Length: 218
Length: 218
Length: 31
Length: 31
Ligand SMILES: CC(C)C[C@H](NC(=O)[C@H](O)[C@H](N)Cc1ccccc1)C(=O)O
Ligand SMILES: CC(C)C[C@H](NC(=O)[C@H](O)[C@H](N)Cc1ccccc1)C(=O)O
Image (cartoon, rainbow over all chains, first blue to last red; front, side, top):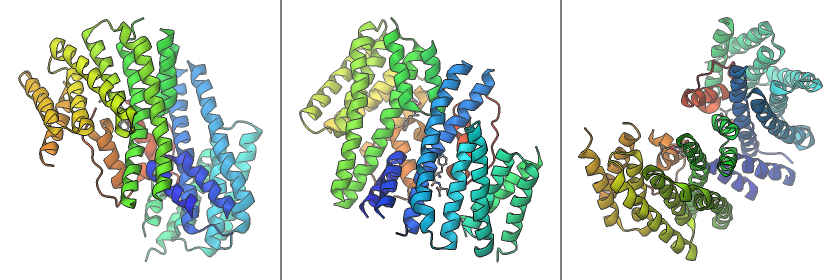
């Protein structure tokens, strides 16, 4: 209960790596991780990996303006290694403790999605066997999330909806097949509409819409 | 020239500690640190210490709601130690390379001010001989900055003006004598007005004004 | 500018955001 | 919400801010 508590301080402080540590500890200590716990843990990794992805994009872009290039390129390297470490950190934890114990629809989809997202982050920057094996692992985590979600969750559900959102960015960006992207996006949007009769869902439906108009306009 | 370059990447990336490292290296390598260099260096420390001061305030506040308290209190500890290390880092550097070589009015005031600000950050959280010796070091760095500034810089100058701003927060907050605070603030504001006949100065004059109306209203 | 350039501004953004129920911490503006 | 909750939003804030002259990096929205 303590490490959770400690988790919220780190979060209040915006010291996210420490938030990770605490949340790792939390899971080993534990049985069925709770909704609160699972969310904290995810927020923590979300922010730690998020800061690296941002810096990585800003530097890659700089590297692009530039063609120095190898300074930039050494630097990106170091950021690239931090990336492997976090994705590494939370992936393992997903096999060992997280996924195996999932007792319910949402929970499996939630975790299977995380797993997808983290291989997805390995895929944005890796280049070799690693990119390939990351693209694949990704496709297959999303897909089994998809099979469960699309069958047990309401189309309006933040998880079904966030899955579809990330799943199709994978296509658009990693596999680089737009077509498959827009269809998955469009599909997930339309059947949320079929059932609109709130508020994490609402955002996500708009992000799908923005991605489509943006993928349509190339 | 390289480490400067590297400095701007770290900055573009918002990896500020690394920005510090680079900027430290930069100074040892160097003779008269340039306006660009001195500013980068300061921005870097500004942000690294800034993030700690923020987390420290948010946690102290939490500690206050709470009277757990000792978790919070261990945590604050660890943040408190990071604080000593950075202030420590840039203080030393100020004696060794920075201040001794200052060739001009602005530069001495600039550095003498930094020195004041960093003892000032030690003072916000230290408690013993250290608070006292930090309060003193602070008063005396600001004061010699003041003597030069108020005599060689225009009242409208970002440095004269930022000095006065921080100098009086020291009184208000550290020495805890308001009176001395408002007078120093008011004075620095009025003679900028006497001479208004832009844009880092303009901001600062408003921060003085906001501090006064806030110190007046207790 | 105040939230970008000042600790007090920053710290206020952050706590408005965090949903923090805690009563106001005391700071003035420094540069 | 988009700058709070999404990488793409965040990264845009940050580069509008940094004064970055660099041409637009390519991203979509993910959660
Ligand atoms: C107008 C200037 C004198 C203030 C300016 N500060 C900067 O460029 C920093 O990136 C942030 N604005 C200050 C900060 C850091 C951390 C938390 C809150 C605010 C500076 O150092 O020159
Ligand atoms: C609506 C939610 C699903 C998104 C939410 N993310 C969070 O709470 C994070 O603190 C930031 N908003 C995401 C972030 C981190 C770093 C950079 C840019 C954006 C989450 O993890 O649940």
